[PDB]
Amino acid sequence: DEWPEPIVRVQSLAESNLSSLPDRYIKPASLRPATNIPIIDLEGLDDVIMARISEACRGWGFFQVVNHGVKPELMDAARENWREFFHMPVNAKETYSNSPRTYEGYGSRLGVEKGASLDWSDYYFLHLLPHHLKDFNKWPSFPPTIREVIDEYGEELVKLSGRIMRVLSTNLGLKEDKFQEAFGGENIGACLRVNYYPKCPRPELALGLSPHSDPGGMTILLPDDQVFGLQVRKDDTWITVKPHPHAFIVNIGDQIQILSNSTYKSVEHRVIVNSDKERVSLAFFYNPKSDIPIQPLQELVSTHNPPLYPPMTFDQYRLFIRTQGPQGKSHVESHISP
Ligand SMILES: CC/C=C\C[C@H]1C(=O)CC[C@@H]1CC(=O)O
Ligand SMILES: O=C(O)CCC(=O)C(=O)O
Ligand SMILES: [Fe+3]
Image (cartoon, rainbow, N blue to C red; front, side, top):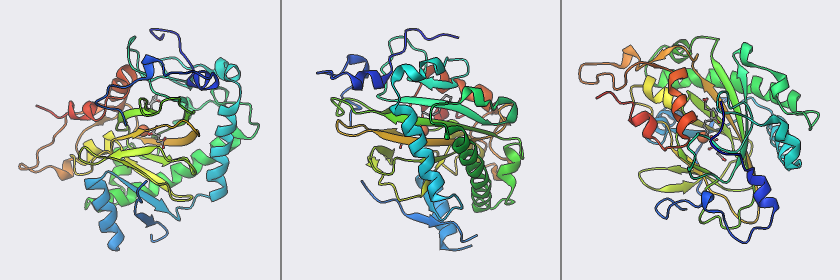
């Protein structure tokens, strides 16, 4: 219900001209900090691409899609509307301050540990589905178009997710609607988190967002179209992702890794910052209905591939990152049954 300490808005620090980086934002030396990602042309519906998509989801846990049915002007309007929101004076969003029991609104940290290291970012969080959680009053207000751009952007990415779910299912040799079934059909969950990474006086000591995999089903990520910062990890190597114009990055989430009995892997990512420019990225979360007990699909279980995770609802699961904040992939790996 409350934070262990008052919230410092990272924008307030960058708007000062601090000579140093506060120790709360200095990461251990062990964890202190752009390559092309092959793109998938989506208006192609059993191609070589189906092998590539499945190859990406199994070894990397992410892929980049172009020609996906979302308007490029809508993609940019979503970014610039949110960028305008974060360019507002800090005290203009303070009334939207979020709290740890729903996290909805204007936030600057994730987790409730009092001494915990912090990330160099502010963010906004809101729900889109289910409808009893959707509330325009908990949305921003200043950019007069922002709520209409959020609603349509959310509508378009819900549609895109349903189509992506069909490719993910088929690539596992399942009925093309098996994932949509496991998530709860049409009453799935959809939320949005927009991340603001202001300039950082010593970015080689800081992280815009510490390592983690997304707890939910899949993430549709719209990274900043101008500034690099997103990094994915492949076998202890942190690789900076060069964004492709008006493409999305599709992230396998923790919930799909569990459903695929670890055939699909959830990507581990982090954000680096820099001293000279900011970043704005949009994270759309497509999640299973939160009271459905999630477990490895029975279709993928043999006696030599037994189910690797016990059942757990997404309501129970999401509290791990809500209480601890980013902890890499230790949340899902501590979920592997003994
Ligand atoms: C680092 C971004 C990952 C997850 C975003 C998290 C928030 O920002 C608050 C809630 C959300 C997780 C949830 O769906 O419970
Ligand atoms: O800033 C980015 O490009 C990625 C944001 C991110 O990692 C997330 O919140 O899912
Ligand atoms: Fe993320």
